[PDB]
Length: 413
Image (tube, rainbow, N blue to C red; front, side, top):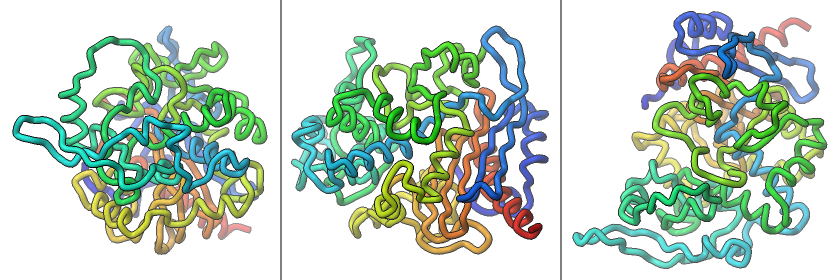
């Protein structure tokens, strides 16, 4: 709830020392860190701490433990969407009304009566794939726009507790006119549905052939993880999370996963840290394993138009700015690319200009720094209750100490 952009995590903290202290404090159980340059010259992979099985037996944390990505799924969904643009099944600016009529049918909630009933406005334009990937569609998580939260409570969910698909779950109005604003929301759950529809298969099938197979990734699954071989390595299948919901990653407040069915491109993927960094690296290298190099290039551009960008930058200064800033400085010029936050200026001895970065829940964070030839992912395996402020510091420790280790390694050849 506070900006942890600069302080002792930024300037002093070392992962080895800080994580280990967090373990013995009993506030985390371990961590998985994976970083690499484009060629695999510099490579840092460290699993620290312990995991607990459902039986209660303990094991040392390990680099191939299966982790809950939570919102780090959004990057992988973004790729699958861009892979459909390559094939010409979609386009970034086309009208999606045909494929996803539910989004065309959405009105823009403008406010409420004193009768407490919604005032709406029809969409000035169709909602596009690009607006889905840049959180400028107008679709917001209800916990980030009170209006949508109010509307969602009034039109109470009848408690017909049946697992719902993406379209059956994010039924709310838009928070602003398509293209004209920015707010974090289910834009990539919608995108993953669009992928399923235009391709005529499940999201997991598509991702498995177009992302995981090219990279040699076999140990992936969306929630719920039914493969017994993966469940044996699931970090979050343990006595504190006997349902493997990802409670420790999302922290308090509830779970993205609980009452859905089908894949959720916004938050649903499980994956090892080792396999996730392969994806980060294929994009750092721009090696044409997932996309053609121009398409990857297009991911590292500011994609919010003037109206959206001001809304983004206003949101970054809102009381929820800390969440949206991913550790960057409140004075660092940023935009939004296809896949995460985009640094627009350079930061000396940290993120290069046009670094893409996002995270998962409160405990996972990733970056791609093409200018400085570094990418990485750090995933804290917390213990409940998850301490949000401490997690920000632990993530900061990763985000800077990995650059520190990079500089040291470069001064050694």
